[PDB]
Image: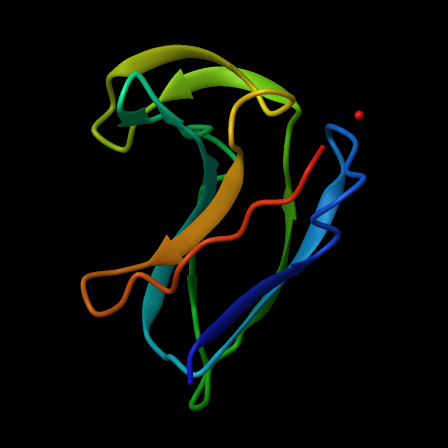
Length: 108
């Protein structure tokens, strides 16, 4: 049912904007590129915002990723720099209803 993809998951630059899509949901969700580190999730306390689906869902917006950024879990505790060149970078989204899963993609 629910599906989450991003146009341009491979051969990505740095401050490049990617087109994210979502279908089979509805409500308010969250997005942002994270990377399982020190056993924590370091995400960019930026490009990370919120969005809402329509009477249907799948909403469509743009998101700019980065090759390297300062680590920072959802909690708010900084972690450290993250190199999407070595660290498993990706973009997840969801809420308390459903995670929605995430997506990786090389980087370069």
